[PDB]
Image (tube, rainbow, N blue to C red; front, side):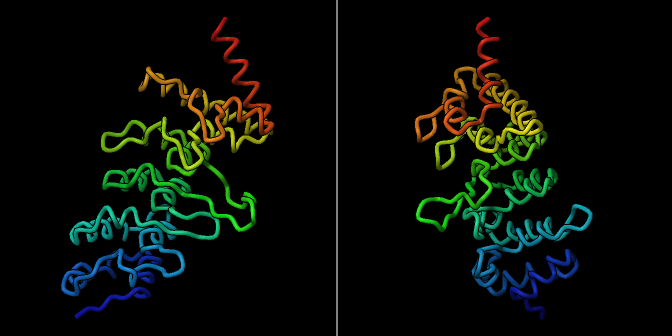
Length: 253
């Protein structure tokens, strides 16, 4: 009968071979194992085979993915499997959903949300200097904030509008930063950057006033006590700052 271990499983999933997964469910069941058990995770990083599949796509797809999710379900393990956190040198708490967004894979973003992905999982920055040296790309930790900061308006739409589990526009990360605070973080002052950050900022403000008319999104304050306007001024984000200021004169006029 058919044995699985970690290098067997990771070789199958990195090749993206659904057929090699035959007998895996039965094996897990008869041996009373799960895909989240340490022997099926990469000891160095915490990665299960799902991040592995999602990092080894062939024409945007890895057909082990649907089969892994179903196996996890049938082993009473689906939420845990989907949300198993991993780490590298830049972030801890990263999940499959973060990867699917970063890789720009809307189809896998949907699949994973549909099957119970944590839409608010935080990819928290790691640091090695006495004071945080900023070696990680800061995008506001959260799945929605990543989609905004990587200019993926369709994923931003899906995440906030889908019929299964919606990411909250008002959500704040470990720094108390909302999506608008994170868009100020990634703002450099180059013109194409000012272009999209500004468009995405304005898109999300409207979206929020539509869904949550009782809330001003740019009023919500991080743990420095700063709005996105004031954070923009403290950190020299001229472009986003002037845009916001210019919008307020318009909306007061």
